Amino acid sequence: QELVQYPVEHPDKFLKFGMTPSKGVLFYGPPGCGKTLLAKAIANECQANFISIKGPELLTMWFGESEANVREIFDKARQAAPCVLFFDELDSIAKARGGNIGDGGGAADRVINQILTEMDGMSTKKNVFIIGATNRPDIIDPAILRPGRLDQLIYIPLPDEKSRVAILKANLRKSPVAKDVDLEFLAKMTN
Amino acid sequence: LSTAILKQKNRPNRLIVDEAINEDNSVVSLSQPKMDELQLFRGDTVLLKGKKRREAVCIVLSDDTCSDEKIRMNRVVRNNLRVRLGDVISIQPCPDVKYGKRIHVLPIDDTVEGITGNLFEVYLKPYFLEAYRPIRKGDIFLVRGGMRAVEFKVVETDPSPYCIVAPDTVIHCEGEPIKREDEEESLNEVGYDDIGGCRKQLAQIKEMVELPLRHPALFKAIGVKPPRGILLYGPPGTGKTLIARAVANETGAFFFLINGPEIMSKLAGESESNLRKAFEEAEKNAPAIIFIDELDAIAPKREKTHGEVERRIVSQLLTLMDGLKQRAHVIVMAATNRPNSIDPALRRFGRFDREVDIGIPDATGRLEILQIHTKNMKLADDVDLEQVANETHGHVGADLAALCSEAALQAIRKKMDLIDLEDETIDAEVMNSLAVTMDDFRWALSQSNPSALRETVVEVPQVTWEDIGGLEDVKRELQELVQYPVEHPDKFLKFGMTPSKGVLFYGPPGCGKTLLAKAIANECQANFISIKGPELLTMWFGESEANVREIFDKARQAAPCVLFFDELDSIAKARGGNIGDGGGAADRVINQILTEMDGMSTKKNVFIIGATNRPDIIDPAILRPGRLDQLIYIPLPDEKSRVAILKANLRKSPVAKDVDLEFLAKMTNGFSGADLTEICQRACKLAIRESIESEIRRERERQTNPSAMEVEEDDPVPEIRRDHFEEAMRFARRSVSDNDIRKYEMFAQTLQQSRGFGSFRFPS
Amino acid sequence: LSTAILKQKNRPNRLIVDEAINEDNSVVSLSQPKMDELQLFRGDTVLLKGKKRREAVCIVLSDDTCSDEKIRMNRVVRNNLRVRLGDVISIQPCPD
Amino acid sequence: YDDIGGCRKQLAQIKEMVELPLRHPALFKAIGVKPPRGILLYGPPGTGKTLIARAVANETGAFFFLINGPEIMSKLAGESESNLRKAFEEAEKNAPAIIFIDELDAIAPKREKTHGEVERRIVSQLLTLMDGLKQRAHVIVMAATNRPNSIDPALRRFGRFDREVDIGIPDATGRLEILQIHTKNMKLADD
Amino acid sequence: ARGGNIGDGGGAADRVINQILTEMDGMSTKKNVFIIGATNRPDIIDPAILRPGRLDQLIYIPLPDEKSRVAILKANLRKSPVAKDVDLEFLAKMTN
């Protein structure tokens, strides 16, 4: 909340102090653990747009032109503020190049580099918040985990006991379920 | 020596105009020495000379009731002079003390209507019957012959400079109604005061031009060669035609504008006729100017040029420009956006050699532009244009007009409750009780896409030394290389030393390797071009040699620059690094930097500073004499520098009184220069949280007693308020571990121990 | 008054569509104070508001038999006002 | 006005930009603020853009003039340019007008598509007419294209097509409005 | 700049030195053009140029010994007004 909502609902507080709003987060956790449902859930709170940017399409850029669409993707979010641009699978290029590639190449990959050019050339006044998500939080380029860019890392753990009850009651909503089913029980053995 | 050209060169008869309490147009207020200085004979007519030759005169009398350097008139003469209060006019009797022969007046409908009568009987006989109310030939003046403002035009007049119109002057009464806005058509002649963000780039125009026009005799006879082409260029929308009109109309020079697309919007074999008929009457009239606007549209590079009928206009333009000879006294100036876009054949000598460079306005250019644009709006008290000028980053001299527009529209939209949708009875107070606040300006600022956020910014930075503190040796050894070779050049000729052309910093990441470059650039008032890592690594992923040349050519036209190539090693570590592959650092880009760093004359004062997080994996070809020569090692901040960094981060935000920065910096030992900026932000997100929680808790609280009427405490948390740093210091992470600062100390110690001739001592 | 232009001026005499069973194409069933608020005398014609300047006017009579909230009209004028039953129609006299 | 669906978010922006300059000419001229010299709508083809222009202009009391794209680029070389003039010439004579140059990416493509000379003489004839507009004429041009970068970049310069709305694909609740517009004649069953 | 005995295998040819060979051979000796090279790594140099008909011999330029250092110092100290009691014969004798 304090990264997507407060810099929107109370922008005057951010002027009383000299604090400057953050422009990035980086979720990382076990794959398939509701890392996408958290971008939408916060985007639903502050009533913001939500542009989703997946793996299999970023990796398309690395197999040809780059740097002519990453410019346009951002300029789409700039005309539709406040967005929550969600670069899913930021490591997708890295593990598709070798995962510590043998020939030597360290971090730069012609596409993650281009995001840096746009991310810096974006005044914080526009309320565009970039959220990444990775399952391999080490091969990610160390040039984005630096102040001024995606700053921190939030670790999304596996659902524990209370989410699993809620996760089940979300999938079983459209399907007529029996009244003697105990989701309070089925969520207590699946551990 | 460079911008000394705007000297005023005062004369004794310079008096600042003022207001007169009498409707009489022929009131003069003088200093007592002024009456008897120019021998001002009472009752005669003295010539008043404004700007753009906008003039109107008055009878000189013994009325010294005003101050010594002020003169009182009413709206007629002052406005016909077209100068405000704060502009002097040389009151001087020109011997043309004469009456007009025949004048023709052009009435303006809204001014004349009300009391109309007959033109002669009501306004021309008695308002001019021996009343010594003089006017100038060819003006649009004001007649206070009725109940309110009544305006006419001067058309015909025997004394061209100035005259008194009498009943001897027979005035034709077939005048036609004119418009208030018709005056604006002629007044589209811009004065000199209407350019902002070009305090510097206008001195260059005042020196290249304005000398060879106001005195053809001087530069013609001495045999010096005036320019015959100026190529202004900058980002689109910085108002260049405005600059051309100012420079032209300000020096009394006919200004003929050739439009860009309006040339090729015409038939094949017809555009050439237009170019010829432009260059052939510009040479005809007077010392003139041609402003070939949007040049890159009628002379692109060869590749964008496709047909032959389009490579004929270019050749016609060339043969017309080489038809300029010293008799013609005509000066052409064009306007592209970058020097590359124009056809290279034009830059050859004799056509478009000298090349001024308008650019993005800087942190005070925006302020002054905003003051230009907002002299018609009715600003509320709490508007602080010095504040909003700091916010607008990428905007140019055109986006600020749109920002003012959006703010005014935001106010006119907050015109909401009680004026009917089709209410034509918009009260005049609506137009004169507008209150544009900071709310409207921030609203507008949040909505405007800036035009030119993708341009390198060449402007003096606003950092000082005590934002770093300490570094008492790097301070001197960086002075001796950027300040001495600028402020004291003669020493470098008295001895034989050639100035160095580079320094290579190296140290742990985030230690002030940028604040040092900005600080030293500030010290000697030198522009500061910064080239970050991605802006190079992008070059390594495609073309090279097409931007690096551009970077150095940009640096050349802003001497003295301090070009700062941050992360020089970026390619070397993005190409494996220290393991990599087969390569002797072998870079497609760095080699280009070497090529341009050799072909660079030392006399131009362009000092190149690098910065590498790793001092060894870099190419050894730069660390060779003649290029970036010596290495400065920037250590981690130690004691005074940490206090300075904390007090420079906490200078924007309200801090408490007992916050002991002198202790906080005394405790945190191994902290970077960018890990004390998260003990100073994460100490503010623990206050934004607390204030924005207390507000909501108070709001939900008082719904228990909505009738209390004693609510809304002024401030729950006004202050960063120690016991926040107590908590924010729980998320303080040392960036550089002690196992990684060894690699730099055990390098710097190796630069030493290869030195020390010590016991060296000349004999006797 | 420097924060005011967005007024639409909703009126106390705004008349909403009500169905009629009459066949006369310019008879209006109005509120009782309709002749009274603007002092609307008999002998003139009002300018009923539709959309797109595509309107249809009536002869206004002292026929105030309707209620104070709506107007009873046939198909002709309301539809020839180029507004379906469900569009705002405002009453205003026209001295033409 | 109410025959447009799924555009309530963007059609609000056209409300602020156009009707205030058009139904209150004096207020702009009095305060001196300047109305836009041209809007540039853009979105995927067939989202009903040539209707929005009629919507805005048919209910604000403003003469409307439609210039088609293929209508211009299909006449004799040298006759098309005349038709552009006899449109701007005629519109300026009339009331506050709205010229809607539909299919603008056909009469002014990227240069990289323009190859003939007469193909680049219409574009210039357009630009001189556009910048020939000033506050006297009281005309507000507005265009339509599918993607913003598929237009000649010389048009976006200031004074021609400065500001640029973006009609987008209708959202999940926008469609419900459209379907209730195209089925107000059908006899839908109760189910 | 290619690897210094590059790993992938490439032995001598580098697309540029080869061109220098092609032009060097196609140039009659009558024209008085003398080609002087200079290298710091005199083993990785392509063995196809150290062949008769091309750059033939090698001359090893040693470090300055005692007199060349005096001359170098007096050449560098020419434009700068020096004191008259400076002993370059000593400063060139310690720097070894």
Image (cartoon, rainbow, N blue to C red):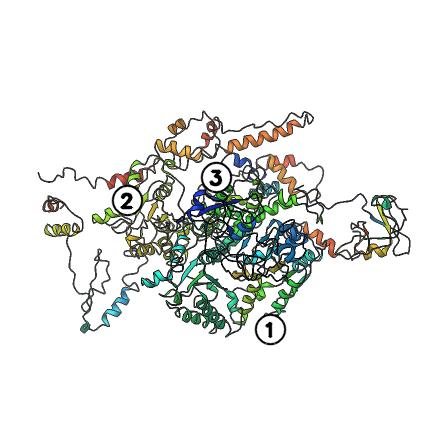
Q: Is residue A158 shown left or right of residue B503? A: right
For mark 1, name the chain: D
Residue B336 screen position, x and y as percent: 45, 60
How far is mark 3 from mark 1, CA to CA?
Answer: 63 Å
Q: Quadrant of residue D71?
A: bottom right
Mark 2 Cα within 10 Å, few/some/many (few <14, many 20+)? some
How far is mark 1 from mark 2, CA to CA?
Answer: 68 Å
For mark 2, name the chain: B
Does mark 1 fall on the same chain as mark 3? Answer: no
Q: Residue furthest left?
A: B764
Residue A154 visible here: yes
Residue B615 visible here: no
Q: Of helix, strand and loop, which one carries label 2?
A: helix
Q: Is residue B427 shown left or right of residue B30? A: right
- In the image, which is nearer the foreground, mark 3 or mark 1? 1
Q: Is residue B45 above or below residue B387?
A: below
**Residue for badge 2:** B484
Considering depth in this image, is A125 or C57 the residue closer to the camera?
Answer: C57
Task: Give amino acid for label 1.
Answer: Glu
**Residue for badge 1:** D79
Residue D133 screen position, x and y as percent: 59, 60
Q: Is residue B592 above or below residue A88?
A: below
Task: Give amino acid for label 3.
Answer: Gln
**Residue for badge 3:** A152
